[PDB]
Image (cartoon, coloured by chain):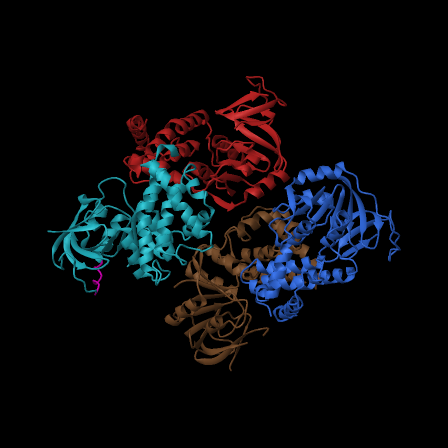
Chain colours: A red, B cyan, C blue, D brown
Amino acid sequence: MSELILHHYPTSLFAEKARLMLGFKGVNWRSVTIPSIMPKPDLTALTGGYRKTPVLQIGADIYCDTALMARRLEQEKASPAFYPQGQEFAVAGLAAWADSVLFLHAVSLVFQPESMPVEQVKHQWPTFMSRLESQLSHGGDFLFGAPSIADFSVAHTLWFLKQTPVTAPFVDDYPSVSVWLDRVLGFGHGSLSDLSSAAAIEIASNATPAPLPDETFIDPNGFKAGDKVAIAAVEAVEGELMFTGREELILRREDNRAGVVHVHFPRLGFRVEKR
Amino acid sequence: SELILHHYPTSLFAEKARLMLGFKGVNWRSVTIPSIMPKPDLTALTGGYRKTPVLQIGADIYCDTALMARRLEQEKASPAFYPQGQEFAVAGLAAWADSVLFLHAVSLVFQPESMPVEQVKHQWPTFMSRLESQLSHGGDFLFGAPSIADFSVAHTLWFLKQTPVTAPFVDDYPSVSVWLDRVLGFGHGSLSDLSSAAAIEIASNATPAPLPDETFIDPNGFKAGDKVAIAAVDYGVEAVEGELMFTGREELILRREDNRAGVVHVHFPRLGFRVEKR
Amino acid sequence: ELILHHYPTSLFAEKARLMLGFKGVNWRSVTIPSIMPKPDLTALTGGYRKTPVLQIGADIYCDTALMARRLEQEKASPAFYPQGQEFAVAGLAAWADSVLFLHAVSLVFQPESMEQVKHQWPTFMSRLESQLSHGGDFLFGAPSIADFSVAHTLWFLKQTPVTAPFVDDYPSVSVWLDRVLGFGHGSLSDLSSAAAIEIASNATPAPLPDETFIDPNGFKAGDKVAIAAVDYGVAVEGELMFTGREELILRREDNRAGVVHVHFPRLGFRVEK
Amino acid sequence: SELILHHYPTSLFAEKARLMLGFKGVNWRSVTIPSIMPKPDLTALTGGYRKTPVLQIGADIYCDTALMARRLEQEKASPAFYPQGQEFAVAGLAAWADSVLFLHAVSLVFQPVEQVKHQWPTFMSRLESQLSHGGDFLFGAPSIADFSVAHTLWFLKQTPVTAPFVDDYPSVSVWLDRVLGFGHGSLSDLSSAAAIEIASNATPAPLPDETFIDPNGFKAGDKVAIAAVDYEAVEGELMFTGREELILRREDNRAGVVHVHFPRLGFRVEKR
């Protein structure tokens, strides 16, 4: 009931970073395969309706957003660190930038007919890569020296390019970049055991949610524990707020199959509204 | 003596060959080629054909996955890519999947929606429903026993599985999805990395295998000893020049001498390749 | 309202399933969890593992044999035990559920075998075929709880193609089997393990049946007893509300479910003070 | 040479061999054994020892699940059945599981039950205790022992009434899911007729390079019969006597020359 459970579609390119993250942490995990097909009732039984995946379940706690997932893992196994001491702000920021701008570029490059506004993406790509090549040319192991969540965010974008002969040069034309990527990819996926989605529900149902964090925080919007709330990504999830924090929001819901569950959201990328 | 595969490891396009190695249960060497042009260690063996994956055994180089299957079949007969009594039917189905089916699958995936298509979208359900109808009967594989055809069909589906948006193109037919996992489950076999340079040396030290004893009269009058170029019909640019050593029902063999790799025999199928006198 | 707790996937639960269809009732189905811990069930049950288990309100009925009898009470027709054939029907059914069934699981689970199960089996089948050869609808002419017991084992065999021939090779048998399976599972609606509990704490147990019994072991209501299954017991503490010819009843207090009555048949259950 | 397993698909006992194949990850061919007798096709290969499952590679036939593991180990080394430096401890635990634990489980499922039930909790609590430490497998790295134990538990759970014996000790489930997680691997059907032909066409593998003095004096070239200890003896020429193995040559009308492999343990060798 305290096992790390990942809800994902195993063949998806988009889910690769989460698996790599587990690989980096060297942990055992349970793999729950989710449907490509709508709807995904077994999944929303845990989520309350949030369907972007991967999702991480530990017992009766559900964690939404890979970015949040990274932090939760950090609580689970400190070492090696996603966020190395003294670089916390810098790492997160680079990681967020990669997750947005870099990722967008990479996917636009790959998913177009020539691989069998894109023009602006092509136009911008070289500056990003040349800058990466330049930093790497100095022989550092990782972007921040020591490995961090930022490597995975950048590495994930590059993984798409490596998929086809046509897109591979976008990474490969810069040699230093290529060696670095193999190093991040070399982390693996950890060790996984298949789990049914049915069982996953049963585990949540049996289990009791973890104790809330002791952090004291004043919500800039005056949201407080006990408030009835809905949270949505920028399918909203309805529930009772249990916590407001610098990094997370926790909401409580009861499900007919899964029972009482706590769903975690990061502040960033999510909006909270009253009801 | 070792089987050597020259490929790009992360390429979706090279998956079928890897599965082929898995089905055979053979141990092979993996040579990781460059995405970037040109590919000198590769053309050192090929003579400039650059479509991979490519199969090397000693100083014999095999081009085209369709040919590769037959060479494999020679190396390990069972389990068979072409089951007895179903040979023509299997080859034809694979050829169809390799072209028509593959084309649809790639069109669907490599479009912006995933991050003439309309015709492809219109067509796709006809193929999938048919496949679903056959599988619903509980047959393990397309022809009873497994075949090169399962792989050819499976390879196309593998592209769809890559994306959440495209996965329903497979997942909507349950029988297909089960079958697909079975085909993918043969895996890639057992590999050890081999450097590209090491591969050239192996060719140099090796000597090309004896030619087939088959007797055939070429349709176009080509004969052993003619000076020839061979090119893929699609990609006339990378023609390969040499001395025709064998012309056969399934095969053309050409001898060339490379400054690094030495004397080498390069094998091409009749299908998809053109022979020009030189 | 009628609820079954079972494993919908389990081959073993088919019999309880066929029973409801035959009575044609509407029931609510609580799936029993695949993972190991099954507290959702045990709160009602108080410790009895084996399924299916039948719940009405605050009364839990353990053992399908008993279940058939409570069913009989709930809707009388068609009867599980036809009038004037009651003993014979119970016996054959008990024989099938024990001997015939055990042979069938063995044939499946232990096909390498030769008491020699494979050696025995043809005798049972040739006998069934002969009786059936007479155009009988059902084993006792009217349909019986007995037909289900026999049918269930045969169906189990047919679920795997290798074992099918054990059934399939007897032709008259096949027809009869289909007629039995025709009853289907009736009509069901899903229900939470959670919901069921609320009904237990919410509801009150039905009134005790009233018959006078001299319990052979001097067991009388208000004694504190543990009731345990003889074959696979690991017991259920409680207080004996009732000791009867067909039933024994236990009251227990459960924190989630509060006060409930558990019903056990006399056969296969041991009582202790 | 392909890996061929002849087995009863529904047999609960046959699952251990199936699991072993999956752990190894080497694709295999599946020949179903008919529930009927005669089984002229299997017998042709083994000479009648009918205990199954059986592993066939060409003209070499391996009997006994423990022997199979060693043969598989030779075929592909990793992941190992017998991790280096733990080999004896692993073999012994596995043998113990194969006998005492498995026998307890069969008793519960199909039937000294009281003694069995009385005993079982000791084994299970001991297993929970080791498992609570959070190690991945029984010897750390996965081993043959994990399957032998896991197999008996899976067996228990095949029928609902007996599942509580596993279920009642919840700590074991995480390790159990993980062992069972390996699966059966990649299998495709092969007909018994086709299997016989594979044997007929093949020639037995080279004998092992081992010098050994047989304790009872048997020698290569001796003519013998080999039987299970509690039992139907196949008759032949003793090709090899070794520390783990005895190899028997026999000839069959359809099969042709075939080599049958037996472990020393559990088999009696007679000068016959």
B125 to the left or right of D164 = left
**Residue D71 location, x and y as percent?**
45, 64
The reply to whether residue A79 is visible in this rendering is yes
**Residue B116 location, x and y as percent?**
31, 36
Residue nearest the viewer, comparing D37 with B240:
D37
Q: Is residue A38 above or below residue D10?
A: above
Tell me the chief SS of the magenta region.
loop
Please identify the quadrant where the N terminus of chain D is shown: bottom left
C67 to the left or right of D204 = right
Magenta span includes B160: no
Q: Is residue B164 above or below residue A251?
A: below
Residue nearest the viewer, comparing C156 with B194:
C156
Q: Which residues are magenta?
A: B206-213
- Taking the spot 20% from the left edge, 56% from the top edge, the residue there is B252
Q: Is residue B212 above or below residue B94?
A: below
C192 to the left or right of B277 = right
- The answer to which image quadrant residue C57 occupies is top right
- Taking the spot 45% from the left edge, 67% from the top edge, the residue there is D192
Spot the residue most to the front.
C135
Residue nearest the viewer, comparing B77 with D234:
B77
**Residue B149 location, x and y as percent?**
35, 53
The reply to whether residue A2 is visible in this rendering is no
D216 to the left or right of B208 = right
